[PDB]
Image 1: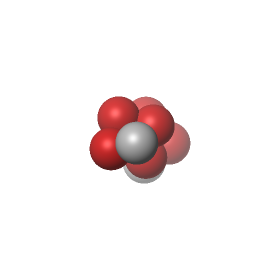
Image 2: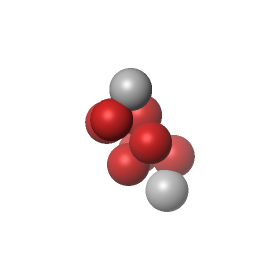
Image 3: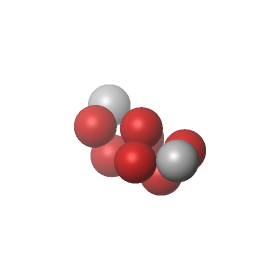
Length: 9
């Protein structure tokens, strides 16, 4: 979840 937030942004 954490990495997917960073990736999205």
